[PDB]
Image (cartoon, coloured by chain):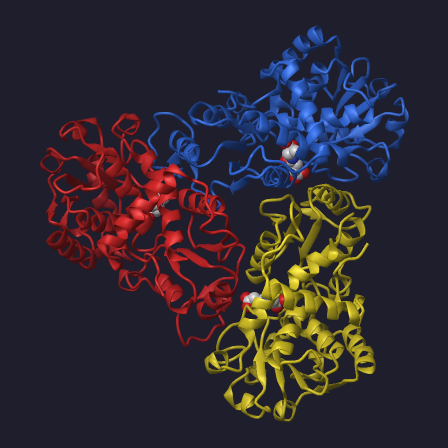
Chain colours: A yellow, B red, C blue
Amino acid sequence: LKHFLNTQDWSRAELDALLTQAALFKRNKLGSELKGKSIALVFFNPSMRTRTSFELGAFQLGGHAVVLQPGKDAWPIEFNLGTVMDGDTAEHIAEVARVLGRYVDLIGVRAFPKFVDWSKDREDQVLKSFAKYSPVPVINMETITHPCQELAHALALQEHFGTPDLRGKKYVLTWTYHPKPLNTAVANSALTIATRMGMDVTLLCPTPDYILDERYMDWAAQNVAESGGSLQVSHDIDSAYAGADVVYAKSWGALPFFGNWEPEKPIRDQYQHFIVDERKMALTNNGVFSHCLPLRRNVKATDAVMDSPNCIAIDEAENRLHVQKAIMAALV
Amino acid sequence: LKHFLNTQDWSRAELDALLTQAALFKRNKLGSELKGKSIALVFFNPSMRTRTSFELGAFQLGGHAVVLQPGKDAWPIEFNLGTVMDGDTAEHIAEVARVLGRYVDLIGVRAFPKFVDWSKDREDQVLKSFAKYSPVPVINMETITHPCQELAHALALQEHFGTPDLRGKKYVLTWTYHPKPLNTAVANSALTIATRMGMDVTLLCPTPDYILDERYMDWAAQNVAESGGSLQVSHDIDSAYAGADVVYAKSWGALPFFGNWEPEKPIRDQYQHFIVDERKMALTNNGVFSHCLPLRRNVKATDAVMDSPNCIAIDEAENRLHVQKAIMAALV
Amino acid sequence: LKHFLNTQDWSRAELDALLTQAALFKRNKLGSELKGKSIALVFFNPSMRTRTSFELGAFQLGGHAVVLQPGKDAWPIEFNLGTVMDGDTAEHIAEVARVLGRYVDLIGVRAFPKFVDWSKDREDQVLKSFAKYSPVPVINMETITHPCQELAHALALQEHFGTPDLRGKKYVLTWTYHPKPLNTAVANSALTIATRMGMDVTLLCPTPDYILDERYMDWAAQNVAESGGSLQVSHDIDSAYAGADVVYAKSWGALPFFGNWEPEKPIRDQYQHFIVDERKMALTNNGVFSHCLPLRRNVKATDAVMDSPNCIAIDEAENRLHVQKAIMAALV
Ligand SMILES: CCC[C@H](NC(=O)CCC(=O)O)C(=O)O
Ligand SMILES: CCC[C@H](NC(=O)CCC(=O)O)C(=O)O
Ligand SMILES: CCC[C@H](NC(=O)CCC(=O)O)C(=O)O
């Protein structure tokens, strides 16, 4: 059974076919690939874009999406095996995934790490649990990676540059400020897709502490070798932006500080200058800027940068709808 | 771009055409005016009628409605310009409105005032923000005015009296009791539509403190002059009800006490007799009674008054569905 | 007007016709029995299966379901008559049921007892209130009985045994452990449907304190007399399981302790051995096991029992979808 957990699990040809079908769906939005079909959208965390695009995406293809939020409307779910369920969780994922499997044709799931222990969050328990027990394809709506975002980001870049071949472009994935430590998911996905597309990637971040988990640094290396791009870590702002064609910002908490954020606050707090402003975008080769959203103005990027015609954040967000309809159509 | 923020922004002919299309949709509920289309229903406050009628309204016209609740399922939204977003709001309306604009064909929004400062609530920031940044038509689902309610109220009166011309009817908008201070929105809308229809309007309320914001008292005066009706403020119960053809109740907090309700409790508390009962309805010319709902029995109106065949509250509520489908059809 | 509050209110022929239409819908899932129609699903408590199956059920028949949660998105509802509404409830069921009646074609409602007073919970106020004031058919989505579960349970048994005639089978409804006292609804429904089908029913429970309300024990007696089955209460585990063909587990709080659970904790706590494990299922005549779900593993039933091929819990859950589409089709 084929799922959509990570773009890394898919071949370049399949990914390419997906992006092309996404471009096609963008030209003809209404269809019947999901006629009479349905998808269960399971959200363990907030969402505006993902929830809306999937729900409309299912409607436009003749299907229906059922939105569930364990702990809110649906019963809380247990993922650990062989445990005694006398706590807060009412039912086990082994039952939930099989029950949903009898109702829907697809299951999407969103579950952010708990932030208490990266050693456990990095295992991707929820996503893997759904894929293991569900008899129908599973779609990652963001856990420790954000594959749907990757394709919406990629398509937006190919549209911008007028070509599917992004090789040669100087790509800069820069960490940015936020009063609190966030999930690395989007950052991990960005590095994965930028290198998979064969671009010259520079992971700009404050200190070595903010470097992404090895799993993704290695995925990137393997992608560079195969795609013909390059990987580079940097702690110097100006040099990174130098001649960049694309700038993707995202804030996240230093992995080494998981479960012990108190001593991390003072550190991230001394790097508020990482905010993307006009000066930094000026050093780029008339580069394009984007962010996965939700974005906090004058914190992650300035008003001017967001209002800039070089900001393709809205196009990328729109592409979530088209790229996701392509994933669903391919999974059924 | 045409929106539906207030009936005041629309001409009498357009309003008339809307009410007529609403009457038509009521005869033939299923259609295709919204086939393959969608609407984002953004709720910052509770709702039963508005949420249900819009969702069914979209379904019956071939479209789909996506229901969002910032702070609950979707991310919290910032509306102030040029502020530093390091607080509770995760993204700005400038992005949210443009993102939704790429997904849906219509955006409805409901946002009650904060009740801390009428000087700020009266600006209608949320509604104006959506209309300013959205590339698609915006619909007021109640903020400081409740335009959809107005048309559902109007149509229900025209049906009741068997004619679209309400001129000459004695209309009484009476304030009523409630343990807490409420939004003036419905009251402001009632005054606006009753005078716009050319009726003889009497705003009955406890003390001059409970008179509506000048903006609406002036809208009413302009409407009277043009529609051929009349406006009158009153603090005397029996005289107001005298020969009235229509009685519309609604409770609200005295504007002068916004942000300082403590000294208002004792005042509203000494006017519980404003409740609409059989005696007051007896003084009317066999008048009809209604309320926007949700209505608290034996507080705003008595059980007998609600069970009375003169209570057209349920018809008015039903009309929300028909009048709204007419607004959506006209906006797309 | 015909509703679906309890299977007890329906004749055997009607119930049979329902189960058969459910079997038919299972073979042909898409239809038009609810084309252009809609149903309001009112949830006062959590739900995953009921909410999902009804929503998909309505979609598959050409209709649309609007999901409401009073106190969350919709306004809180008052059910007591002639009370003064100055509390937390914003509107009365007399209005809510009539308003919904103008919007939808069907109303489903889920409302668990408050657990403070069984004398009041047993009256089934919410369900009866909806059925009394609504101009459209009402469907019990679980209050003090769970009729939709009953039919999904029944159909699953008829499929398992390859026949609609379950007479002769040894049916065991056993109470099981849970750290907290739960609703008796499912237990009451199980006893009602098992005896209505004419099986040899044994209500196995810890102490006489855990025997179900007389209303249901009497319904069972009347059903036994008519269906040709038998009823029996037991406090002995091994004897009950002896040669059973079906084992249905469910945990619930002792009725006599309603509103005073403190002294009940220690009692239920000394009966954790009621958990359904391999040993007990071994004493059965190769019996089938099921539960309504959500089920807490290694508390109500062990992992082995749930993973056992004799566990038909997932089939029963799937049947909720088919049996409910049959109820809606019959009510419209
Ligand atoms: C279908 C059963 C619904 C509900 N179940 C619960 O309340 C169990 C919840 C828990 O275990 O936390 C009940 O017992 O009536
Ligand atoms: C698409 C990004 C989702 C999420 N974002 C947040 O949690 C930011 C929320 C905030 O700024 O309050 C994240 O960082 O993974
Ligand atoms: C259609 C009216 C919506 C809202 N009503 C309330 O907030 C009343 C709620 C309550 O009585 O608790 C208002 O007054 O504007």
Q: Is A192 displayed left or right of B321 in the figure?
A: right
Instruction: Provide residue C178's location: percent of width, then percent of height.
Output: 71, 34
State the residue at coordinates (81%, 69%).
A11
Give the quarter the ligand 2 occupies.
bottom right
**Number of marks in the rendered image:** 0
Give the percent coordinates (x, y) of residue B196: 19, 50
Quadrant position of the C terminus of chain B in the picture: bottom left
Query: Seen in the image, is A102 located left or right of residue A206?
Result: right
Q: Nearer the viewer, residue B59 or C303?
A: B59
Q: Residue at x 77, y 32 (%)?
A: C272
Along the line of sight, which residue is nearer the eye, B142 or B114?
B142
Residue C281 position, x and y percent, is 87, 28
Q: Quadrant of residue C113?
A: top right
Location of residue C266 (image quadrant): top right
Q: Nearer the viewer, residue C299 or A216?
A: A216
Residue A161, given in percent of the width and then of the height, sits at 62, 82
Q: Residue at x 34, y 57 (%)?
A: B4
Viewport quadrant of the N terminus of chain B: bottom left
Q: Is residue A297 above or below residue C76?
A: below
Residue C331 lies in quadrant? top right
Left or right for A93, reference B141 = right
User: Which residue occupies 50% across, 26% down?
Assistant: C137
